[PDB]
View (cartoon, helix red, strand yellow):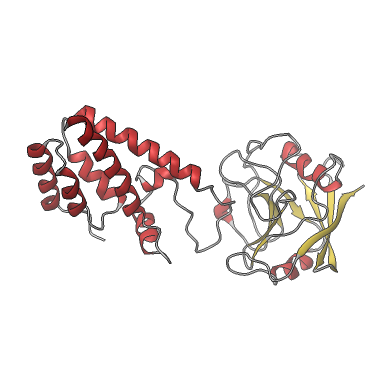
Length: 135
Length: 165
């Protein structure tokens, strides 16, 4: 693991500043976010300055998806067995309540729970909400 | 005495293994102690008699008390709702500690576990409420039926259980 680069970010910043919220933002986001951890996905999103209303629309979708995820994935009984990693909650997938090595484990466990791909799908559904409002 | 003593007679695929008894620390965690004591005597008309240790992890613990679904997804306390973590005064100090299993903070029902090792990292996450008095060797035997993910190789049941004194 290497945290995303200022180089990739600059690109996403240039994308959002020019194209606002045209359909083109979505395929771009997907390209720049290849293999991202949740932490990296949030660093990309945090780089957006302004567009507060649209950023809140994204957050609402992320919160809704995360709660759906919890609903469909009941917590297993603790205590967790030695060696085993706990199952991710919605907030873990979105990066608020998890660490980076946890994200890495899930992504690299057997098989993977690909918490980056999951969170990215939620983000994408939020970007679709924004694109349909603005364009 | 203030602290009650409970016994479980354990069977393996119907065959008697032996008896394990516990001291319940009612003097430190009276609400958690009373739940397990009442489930052990059956006095509320439901409880542990006949239920199974559904998850046994060698070198870690033995877990049971789901007498409603028998697989971890059930359990129910005597209080008509899951109940808060009473306190975390007592620690997970080695084999024979009796502690509550849970699905997060303040979600105690009827599931419990018996430590077969020191598990200090559980301190502050599971409420310790008792300890094995007699029968630790029976606990150690039960551990041989577990596996790394907890699946048991034979049906480990609480054939009978109640209060001593």
